[PDB]
Image (cartoon, rainbow over all chains, first blue to last red):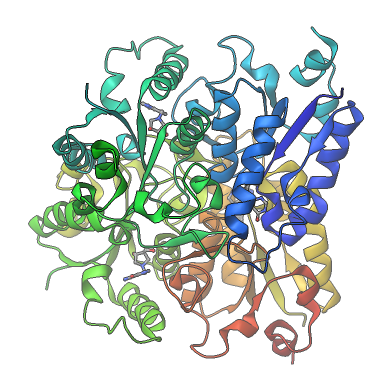
Length: 154
Length: 154
Length: 154
Length: 152
Ligand SMILES: O=c1[nH]cnc2c(C[N@@H+]3C[C@H](CO)[C@@H](O)C3)c[nH]c12
Ligand SMILES: O=c1[nH]cnc2c(C[N@@H+]3C[C@H](CO)[C@@H](O)C3)c[nH]c12
Ligand SMILES: O=c1[nH]cnc2c(C[N@@H+]3C[C@H](CO)[C@@H](O)C3)c[nH]c12
Ligand SMILES: O=c1[nH]cnc2c(C[N@@H+]3C[C@H](CO)[C@@H](O)C3)c[nH]c12
């Protein structure tokens, strides 16, 4: 069975970001052999004319985080997206694999060790957390970083 | 034994907000008979002179969310605080009781049903979610709202 | 005639913050002999039941920034409030006196020199901008900081 | 002389956004015959190892807003970017033309008339401000919207 990554991001909210930013990240993950669950694409069939669609998206996304093997969370922005953060907290509590992506060079932090709010790293090991922290789309395929180690059992 | 509420908020980051905003919320919860776990206060014996303090705070807060009975999440701001959101996601995944506080009247939402990102409500029931959503400090004591129903088994 | 300070803040958006955080700041400024224009208070005779109230607040605040002598901008939050930032940009372009207030210890910055986005400091001097930068309510009345020196022409 | 638009955005902060999002917007503006001043590109010839680079960037952007004819502010995100907002306030106070771009469908507002904080619209007319408000890159070239009309 392929490992399943839930690709959490705010990029579905902007028409241009949805069209241009997500496909390259999806493709980078798929090139490692990962099955990618991207929520904006997976919720295509919900009936958005009905008033309960927001509840139905919430529950579908909760189920996807429960059923994934890891989360790949796009945590660009100041601050990172609140929905992505909820999904990240779910992933941490459910002991999913955690991978963080930030190619935004601004620092937005409450501490000196981590580049973001310390809670985002609570599900990563004390040592080597930066191996799970990706700062460019080109880095996703790196054999030295945590996605590759995960797939190769190292 | 008293129910334990984890009071998640960004109010510890600002000197004035920590001093003035949190004690009234703490007192409102305590007046219901709740034991309040406030993380900015509870992390007062971490050695902040040591470089790992941020990791030890992260783990301490994760353990507190695992051990609470419910979270009372202050979700003021545009957007809500990313650390609060991680803790909220943890609470949802761990089937804790979920209560939300927002006396910020700005609307910051991706949908028409809820006043915030739909993910924040994923741990609340489809019907009656607003019973868990508090919009003033004065409302916390309300016998018609979910904190009181929780405590009285209704 | 008293110097006029426009007190820009997001604190009017939260019921508790409006009641508890703003009066102490207003009072500290007034103790210096300043006439304080606080926008949430100053627009309390607008009819908020009428559809044009938002345009009338915008124009009232535009006029107040044009007519003030200085702006005292509360730039707490990650990021600072977007309305406060528009008013700050107006003040810079109109050669008003500029004073910044941040008692939030988090860093949210795109550079190493300043704790915030470099644009917020465009109306401050290259050297000694920190004299215009207030990090606690108790510091506002300091005779060593720029607000007091400005009022006394020293 | 070609009208000058200052293209304010936070897209320069993210490597992928700077590479992918900004060139299409620049090209849409330039297709209208506009001279586009994009701050992340224009700041290139600043020495970023001299300690004062942040101050120099700030002053250079201030001057570009003073010397543009209009601002085209990308106000995506929740909230819109604080540096874009400072530049927008400068443009309002300096009586520059104002155009806003938001293809982010989330609402982030303190009022019922506008989809964002009311201050962002203080430099736009009470009626017809929507004609200055662009919600897709495709819309930038519309002859029914305010940017094209401003060119005549
Ligand atoms: O409109 C939507 N479509 C699909 N999913 C979401 C969500 C849920 N998550 C949260 C996060 C964006 O907040 C992204 O991973 C999708 C919120 N709004 C929508
Ligand atoms: O500096 C800190 N002190 C204590 N806790 C936190 C946390 C953890 N949570 C997250 C949330 C603020 O982000 C609040 O509930 C405390 C992040 N930074 C700090
Ligand atoms: O409800 C309101 N009342 C008064 N002013 C504003 C503004 C304008 N400014 C902007 C800034 C808050 O965004 C504060 O200085 C007031 C936005 N909303 C309101
Ligand atoms: O690193 C930077 N490069 C170029 N410009 C800016 C600015 C000035 N403005 C502000 C706004 C981004 O905050 C965008 O229009 C550029 C701040 N930081 C930088």
